[PDB]
């Protein structure tokens, strides 16, 4: 039963929340996977960034 983040986790979690073209479903798909493997936070960010870029204008 956790109360608090970790220093790389909070960075990725804020950053994935900050993306506007991301869905209330998609967001959880990177965040949940971040709780699972925080060592790859950089690469989970790269997916959320890419999917926001897919759901942007042309």
Image (cartoon, helix red, strand yellow):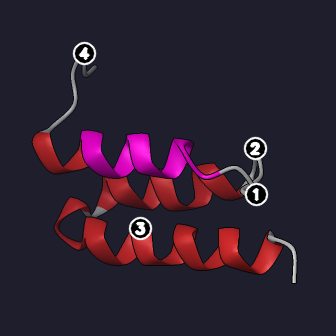
Mark 3 neighbour density, 10 Å: few (under 14) some (14–19) many (20 or more)? some
Marker disc for residue 24: 2
Q: Helix, strand, or loop for circle 4?
A: loop
The mark lying in front, picked from 4 and 3, is: 3
- Residue at the top extreme of this rendering: 3
Q: Helix, strand, or loop for circle 3?
A: helix
Badges 4 and 2: C-beta atoms under 8 Å apart?
no
In this picture, residue 21 sits left or right of residue 6: right
- Indicate whether residue 17 is drawn in magenta: yes
In the rendered image, residue 26, in percent from the top left (x then y), is placed at 70, 58
- Which residue does the image show at 50% across and 51% down from the upper left? 16
Badges 2 and 3: C-beta atoms under 8 Å apart?
no
Mark 1 neighbour density, 10 Å: few (under 14) some (14–19) many (20 or more)? some
In the rendered image, residue 29, in percent from the top left (x then y), is placed at 59, 59
| Location of mark 4 (residue) | 3
Q: Main secondary structure of the magenta part?
A: helix
Question: Does residue 18 lie above or below 50 as drawn?
Answer: above
Res 2 → quadrant: top left
Task: Give, as a single range, the part of the protein colored magenta.
Answer: 10-19
């Amino acid at each position: 039963s956790d109360n608090k983040f970790n220093k790389e986790q909070q960075n990725a979690f804020y950053e994935i929340l900050h993306l506007p073209n991301l869905t209330e479903e998609q967001r959880n798909g990177f965040i949940q996977s971040l709780k699972d493997d925080p060592s790859v936070s950089k690469e989970i960010l790269a997916e959320a960034k890419k999917l926001n870029d897919a759901q942007a204008p042309k």
